[PDB]
Length: 296
Image (tube, one colour):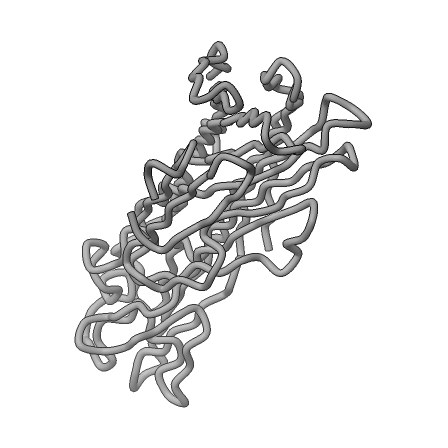
């Protein structure tokens, strides 16, 4: 499946040293691949250990195409939302003090930079400070037609993000989303022709016309900054969740026109892994991966 890489050392100062180890856990069933790069920053001029965790990998769309022989009613499954959560599940000396992205972002390309200044000063910036900075990382991911937003339960011991369908353009029509509704046509999200004479299965817009996130996948890139307050315990635990909410989109003919309906999160697939972060020897250990699913 996957494993942990030996710790790599990168001295920067008499004060600052950087240790890197990478963990990889896969759910082949759900086609979700997590890749966690832990960057331990030991700075002697700061009274707090810092861990800048960068989560990359892949979350499959889950997209189930429609059967082209369906005549009056047809349905499809698409990837409507991708949620990523990082959670420190132990030790009151560990708290999530920062992360990226930190704001709502509807740009086709979410790009941020993490800078660590000698002394424990961290700062995230929208884009791509040198000299003054001891360590820096970047996040870079495409989310065309979708938007990123922080989860609502983000606090001192948890941070999460949601990349949801936002402004999807059918063609010259739209934008549409998971909750669009027209008095007559319903949710026209993936509806091709309103009065089309075609079979239901052949009245959805072309897959290639669909956003990459809707029918292909999402390659996340998020950063979690955690700080250990040199006391209580040298160990802690952290859980990283990658999830996809699969929506059921269906349309049907009533004799005069086509009408669409989108059932939000009608099928959920979730991959969750747990690690033991050894803050003294700067190593992580895999405790448990749990694949789970919900079906309406």
